[PDB]
Image (cartoon, rainbow, N blue to C red):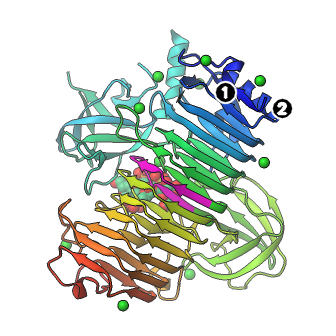
Amino acid sequence: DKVIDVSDFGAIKDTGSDSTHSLYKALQEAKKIGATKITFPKGRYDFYEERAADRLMYISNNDPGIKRITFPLSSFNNLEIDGNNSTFIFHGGLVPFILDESSHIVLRNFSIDFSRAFHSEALIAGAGKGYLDLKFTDQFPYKINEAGILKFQSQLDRLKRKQISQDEYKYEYKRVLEFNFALREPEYMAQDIFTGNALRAEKLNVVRIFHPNLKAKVGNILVFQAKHRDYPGVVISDSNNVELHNITIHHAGGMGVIAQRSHNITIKDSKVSPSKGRIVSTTADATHFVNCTGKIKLIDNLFESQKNDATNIHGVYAAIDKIIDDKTVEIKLQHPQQFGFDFIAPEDELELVHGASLITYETNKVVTSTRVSNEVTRVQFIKPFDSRIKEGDSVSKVRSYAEVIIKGNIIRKNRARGMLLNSRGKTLIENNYFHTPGSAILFEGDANFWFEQGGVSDVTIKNNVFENSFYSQWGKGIIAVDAGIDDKFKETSRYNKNIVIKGNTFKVFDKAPILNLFSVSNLVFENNIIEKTTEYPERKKYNSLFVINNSDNITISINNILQGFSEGKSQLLSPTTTYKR
Ligand SMILES: O=S(=O)(O)OC[C@H]1O[C@H](O[C@H]2[C@@H](O)[C@@H](CO)O[C@@H](O)[C@@H]2OS(=O)(=O)O)[C@H](OS(=O)(=O)O)[C@@H](O)[C@H]1O[C@@H]1O[C@H](CO)[C@H](O)[C@H](O[C@H]2O[C@H](CO)[C@H](O)[C@H](O)[C@H]2O)[C@H]1OS(=O)(=O)O
Ligand SMILES: [Cl-]
Ligand SMILES: [Cl-]
Ligand SMILES: [Cl-]
Ligand SMILES: [Cl-]
Ligand SMILES: [Cl-]
Ligand SMILES: [Cl-]
Ligand SMILES: [Cl-]
Ligand SMILES: [Cl-]
Ligand SMILES: [Cl-]
Ligand SMILES: [Cl-]
Ligand SMILES: [Cl-]
Ligand SMILES: [Cl-]
């Protein structure tokens, strides 16, 4: 009627049977009749590959290919999916949700998990020169083949072997990271150890893995980082007015929520958090927004234990590959996880940017655009473009940049950074808790490897708590700039502008930078409380709370408060150019 009950289409809870086809039929009926809601009788629902719809997808900062989709929400309008706090379990290579060219879609009250994680975890039972001894629990099956290589499996007749073998790709790894057993966070100062996808291994007649760079503390947990990003949790693509309310994402092969080229997204009262027996949630970013517009609201969420940043809101740079004539260029997407990102349309305004400095030469209007491939697009401008532009420079679309509201979130226990603020729109970061091994807030962006467009223009960071963040090495300080500006251009490049950091509590354990800035104009750091702790060992390489280079109009104000420090506030609040002296 107005509300469609998925059990009227044969999806039965708690049985363990596949509910994919019944779900599909309920979705098509909702589109046929104009229903505004689908409800699940509260229970457990399982979804498998065999009857899932298949679609080519490019998904920014994730891996492209054929996706099997359990909720294929393409061209839906004005539809709410209320799971009534049901539990959704996905078996194998599924993308749970893709919202494609949809509008006013509300997702509420369910959880997402996969029956076997894409990553794997092990207890570290011993260590030595070039090896670790590991105990795996049952939920991470593996085989050690005749070659002496550790290969994780989907599960423990010739065609069943063949399909299991075909599953091996999904559980490939590329690096390992040590997690502290007691704190359930990346181990203090441990770093990613690259291994590649094949580790020599042997079972001691416990599994021993061999690699020259292995180093960890016994009793900690070793995480094998999933190599691939093929199965993100919720994809929001070319869509508008999407809300996620009380969604729990226990796991994904890649990001928890990834949005590209969409407009108005809210994520509220949701959580990314591990399920029973796991120390890791999603295998990449909890959330992530590419070329999005309107309001992006992250309200009152819990993001913990994912293998990457909690959020990143940014644009796409594309390199100028070939100059065809004075008015025409071919641009090329650079990073493999950007291939297929079409964004340049007739009448768009583009920034033309010098690659090594991130200085904008000019803006220009595009009159025509032709997609040549999933890499190359040809672009014709209305007037001849600036004569200084060379091949190797980049373009970025001048958007109505997203207004970013990030309020009331708890961000902790994840690998890497807290928030990558590459939002050039009006940005508000207020009343969040950060406990991250990397930079809690990082202004990044580059046009040489990730080709992500950042460059802040209006940022307010007010009344957050930064507790012993940046306790490892993914970043350059608690709040830091690592934008891709060559040293030669730092003094003249001003990439991030107009930043107010007021009313925060920084609980710090050593004298690593609270602020580490370059190429900034107009930043005010006032009315903050800085308070010394002993939560982690002090690192002797840091002796400066405020490292500032190649910036202007930076006020580190006198009205900040310092508690528990040996030295006086006038030494401690005084900027250096270096970490030490
Ligand atoms: O230098 S770090 O800040 O620590 O970056 C970490 C880095 O890890 C791997 O590369 C390093 C290690 O492999 C290490 C092992 O001994 O050797 C180092 O010298 C390598 O450093 S290097 O890459 O700077 O040359 C990653 O490669 S690997 O998995 O094949 O081993 C490498 O890509 C890089 O990982 C990135 O670290 C970031 C935090 O520092 C962040 O998590 C990146 O992902 C997210 O951020 C970027 C924007 O910066 C994009 O938005 C991504 O989509 C986000 O997911 C992370 O990249 S990724 O996980 O490989 O995709
Ligand atoms: Cl009906
Ligand atoms: Cl039922
Ligand atoms: Cl779809
Ligand atoms: Cl609508
Ligand atoms: Cl299961
Ligand atoms: Cl095959
Ligand atoms: Cl659980
Ligand atoms: Cl990854
Ligand atoms: Cl140059
Ligand atoms: Cl943006
Ligand atoms: Cl030192
Ligand atoms: Cl002052």
Does the residue at mark 2 contact the one at mark 1 (Cβ under 8 Å)?
no
Compared to 310, does 328 lie above or below?
A: below
Asked if residue 333 shows in the view, the reply is yes
On the rendering, which quadrant does ligand 12 occupy? bottom left
Which of pointers 2 and 1 indicates the residue nearer the eye?
2
Where residue 487 appears, as percent x and y from the top left, is: 44, 81
Is 67 on the left or on the right of 221, as rendered?
Answer: right
Is 392 on the left or on the right of 171, as rendered?
Answer: right
Compared to 398, does 267 lie above or below?
A: above
In primary-sequence order, the first of circles 2 and 1 is 2
Where residue 22 appears, as percent x and y from the top left, is: 69, 21
Which of the 4 image quarters holds residue 348?
A: bottom right
**Amino acid identity at mark 1:** Ala
Where residue 541 appears, as percent x and y from the top left, is: 22, 72
Is 51 on the left or on the right of 344, as rendered?
Answer: left
Is 554 on the left or on the right of 105, as rendered?
Answer: left
Specify the segment rendered in magenta: 296-313
**Residue positioned 51% across, 61% down in the render:** 406
Residue 33, numbered circle? 2
Nearer to me, 132 or 119:
119
Q: Is mark 2 within 8 Å of ligand 2?
A: yes
